[PDB]
Length: 170
Length: 170
Picture 1 (tube, rainbow over the protein chains, first blue to last red):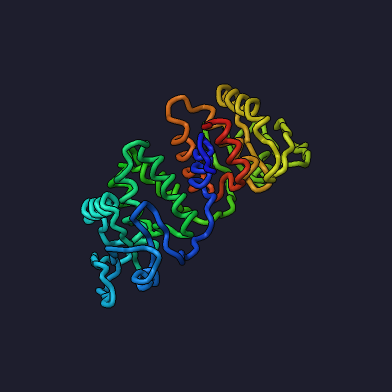
Picture 2: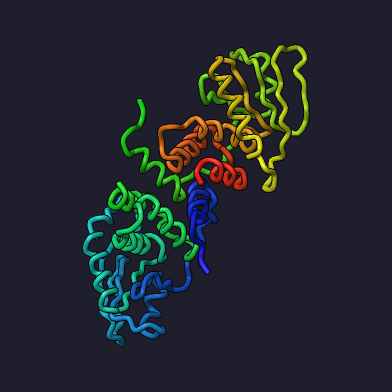
């Protein structure tokens, strides 16, 4: 049971003109594609012993943690969640790595502190990168709002949203 | 001094993903085209003695007022600002009347109580109707956000926005 056929279009245009719930902190991990997951700091601590056989965790926070009782490989890309940091510089490599994970069915968790702005930006970028079908402006609006509806908050950082738009739309 | 060339596009996509100021009540009349104006109840009371030579006022509120010391013609279309009323039924005639006004340079004020939802919807409809150039989805997003940025609040009513989208986009 899904919505097809220009209900998505009204959904999108209404969301695009203010029909948006106030930001609600995301709590549980979200499976976004077959092997790619999106979460927050707690979710990463919880990653050793979750239903998923993670091979990788992509740590987007500033601090290099370990999960030493586990065999998960922790990739650290330290970024700040601010309106000045350039996150686009890592777009190509990160989306490339995530697609490799999806090809090899190697589960990977993409997380930040909140699971909203450094991690949601990389998940958005991945989704945009994998779109060969749909007009980017519309794919962008659909992805953004459906992910926000799902998670409660998604790339609330305006500068991160600007960087995705420039990279993948304009 | 204007923004052209894909700054409008980033502006639009950012506004479309949550970059929106909280609704602020509009106070002064807004000239939207050469002879078409948008305002609230006070603005209409003030219409007899304003810098503009109104020939017409389009009263979208429920109550039939008069301005008996004036020669302004008051057209009454009574509508409620609610999430159930069908405003689309008057779209064709209203936009037709407004375009005639613009052709004959006959100044006309479009108002409701707030100057935000019954009146902004008819102004939006007019603008959409007069667009023969731009893709409707994009013209819609541009008009909506630039009018909201200008006025402070514009078609905040979600059902009125749905009706414009259905009429003019889908």
